[PDB]
Amino acid sequence: GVDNKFNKEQQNAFYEILHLPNLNEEQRNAFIQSLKDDSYIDTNNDGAYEGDELSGSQSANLLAEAKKLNDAQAPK
C-alpha cells in the first residue's frame, strides 16, 4: 500500500525516445504510453494525469525496443 514515483532510470529513457529523428507519432505515443502505463499519480491534484505526471515503468525494455525500431525503420 505504497505510492510509486516516475524514477530516474525511466525519465532518462523517456527522453531518449523523445530524441528519435524522422518521428512517427503513432509509434512515439505507443512507446511513450507504455512508459506511463505501469502505475498512475495526480501529483498536482487537478483531477487529471498530465505532463510531468506521465513517466514510471520498466522503461529499460521499452527503450531498447523503441530504439531498435527507430533504427530498423530508419533510412539507409
Image (tube, rainbow, N blue to C red):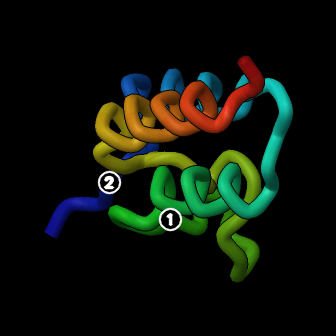
- Outermost residue toward the top in this view: 76
Q: Is residue 56 above or below residue 3?
A: above
Q: Residues within 10 Å of mark 1 (few under 14, many from 20)?
A: some
Which callout, 2 or 1, points at the residue further toward the start of the chain?
Answer: 2
To which quarter of the image does residue 43 belong?
bottom right
Observer able to see residue 7: no
Residue 45 percent coordinates (x, y)? 67, 69
Disc assigned to residue 41? 1
Front one among 71 and 23: 71
Q: Is residue 31 above or below residue 13?
A: below
In the image, residue 35 sits, relative to residue 20, either above or below, namely below
Determine whether label 2 and label 1 are within 8 Å by CB: yes
Check disc 2 and report its element: helix, strand or loop.
Answer: loop
The amino acid at mark 2 is Asn
- The spot of residue 56 in percent (x, y) is 42, 48
Of all residues shown, which one is farthest toward the bottom? Answer: 47
Q: In the visual, does 32 lie left or right of 5?
A: right
Say which residue label 2 marks. 4
Q: Which residue is drawn at 60% across and 23% down?
A: 16
| Disc on res. 22 | none
Residue sitting at 37 percent across and 24 percent down?
9
Identify which residue is drawn at 32% across, 54% down: 4
The x, y position of residue 63, in whole percent, is 44, 33
Frontmost residue, 4 versus 34: 34
Residue lying at 55% horizontally and 53% vertically, measured from the top left: 31
- Amino acid type of the residue tagged 1 in the rendering: Ile
Identify whether 3 is placed above or below 17: below
Left or right? Give the position of 58 relative to 63.
left
Density class for disc 2 (Cα within 10 Å; few <14, some 14-19, many ≥20) is few
Please, what secondary structure does the residue beneath circle 1 have? loop
